[PDB]
Image (cartoon, rainbow, N blue to C red):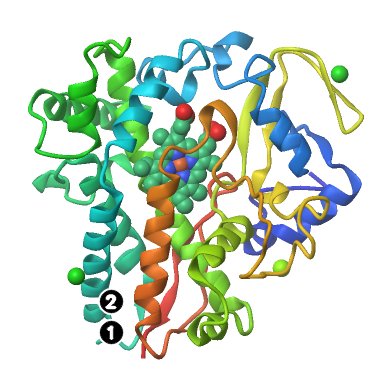
Amino acid sequence: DPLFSPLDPAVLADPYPVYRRLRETHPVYWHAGLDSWLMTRHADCTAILRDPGRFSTDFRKIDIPTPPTLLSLQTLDPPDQTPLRHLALDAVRAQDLDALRKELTLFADQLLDELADRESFDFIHDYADVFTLRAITRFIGVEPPETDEAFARFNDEEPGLRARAHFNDLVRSWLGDPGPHGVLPDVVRLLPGSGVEADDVLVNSVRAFFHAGFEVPSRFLGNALAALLATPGAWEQLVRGDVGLDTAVEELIRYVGPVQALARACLQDTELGGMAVKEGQVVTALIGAANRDPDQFPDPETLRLDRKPNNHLGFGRGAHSCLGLNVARIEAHVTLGALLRHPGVRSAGEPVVRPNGTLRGLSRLPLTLG
Ligand code: HEM
Ligand SMILES: [Cl-]
Ligand SMILES: [Cl-]
Ligand SMILES: [Mg+2]
């Protein structure tokens, strides 16, 4: 594609200038390769996410079958998704976030204090993945299986179907013998009377919940630090106390939030950006691009850690909006405060970007804490 190739190495290195220039000329662009419309403006993406009867997550409504092991909260739309959405909401909001902050603060300090002895380490492998895996396991209330303590088989065909079937077996065992605390034990207690059947959709939803709370936050933590180190003065601003962590975390989500694209199936003919989107077509909300839309954010390509207001789309919108956003904020807030407790945070090599145009993240972030 002459205007946007998500996986072109030069694009992956810095996709935002490409996003910007696509937005300036074709804010609603039909991409033949991806076979989808590409919306790069905040207003269009917002409208795509807030009309489920017009833009659905259930691609069966345009007659594309859903694999049985992937029918879940994420691939259902109201009213089918409603009971599961509320059950998951109820289970999450029963969790003690203050207790989670306190124990994550401990873990972060332990990890970094051990890594402080290295001359150079990979922040992704040694912190982001380890930190976020501990957080999601504790939050859900399950223990890593001794034979796959990192859940590596499920990080992602028959192998694929076998991994998801194995994970579903673990979930059913968890549901049958819940631990003393966490989202999953609360789901079990809340399930009777929820309008949700303990069936494959529930099991699949627990699997999706785990992935939503593992790979996405891990990728964000890496992206955020990389942006702080690559933006002159950004880290020093934090070290000096010039900006508050709360606003800085929200600006980092807008600036380099990992979710780049949210696909929806068009169920009704709609005109967007002067383009005739037709029923049966796929639309992709490039929320990574929308979060740098100059119509919504002044100086959008500039990292302003004190930015206010900041109506970013990094946590989605509407019926499928993120349910773990307060956990994600605690994780980022804890990580930054823990890093700030070290006097020499600096890069120690070039970052390496994952070849992913949908969920942006780094595979290596060489770093040293001094
Ligand atoms: C920086 C971290 C995170 C970011 C940027 C993020 C972002 C998002 C976004 C954009 C969506 C919307 C997906 C869509 O509309 O299709 C979403 C959905 C979701 N997120 Fe997060 N998320 C993060 C962390 C978490 C964590 C830690 C959890 C679990 C505790 C979580 C649980 C979920 C769930 C369950 C959904 C699906 C809601 C539904 O489909 O009804 N997220 N997230
Ligand atoms: Cl402590
Ligand atoms: Cl219209
Ligand atoms: Mg730039």
- Residue 189, visible in the rendered structure: yes
Name the side, left or right, on which 306 lies relative to 170.
right
Total tally of numbered discs in the picture: 2
Task: Check disc 1 and report its element: helix, strand or loop.
Answer: loop
Look at the numbered discs 1 and 2 and tell me whether their residues touch, using CB distance below 8 Å.
yes
**Residue 15 image position (x, y, % from top left):** 69, 58
The residue labelled by disc 2 is: 112
Label 1, ligand 2: CB separation under 8 Å: no
Alpha carbon separation for disc pair 1 and 2:
6 Å
Judge whether 42 appears above or below 166 on screen.
below
Q: Is residue 34 visible?
A: no
Task: Say the numbered circle drawn on residue 116.
Answer: 1
Name the quadrant of the N terminus: top right
Residue plotted at (7% across, 28% down): 177
* Foreground pick, 244 / 359: 244
Does residue 255 sit above or below 289 in this rendering?
below
The x and y percentages for residue 277 are 81, 21
Ligand 4: quadrant of the figure: bottom right
Q: Residues within 10 Å of mark 1 (few under 14, many from 20)?
A: some
Find numbered disc 2 in the image and state the secondary structure of the residue it sits on: helix
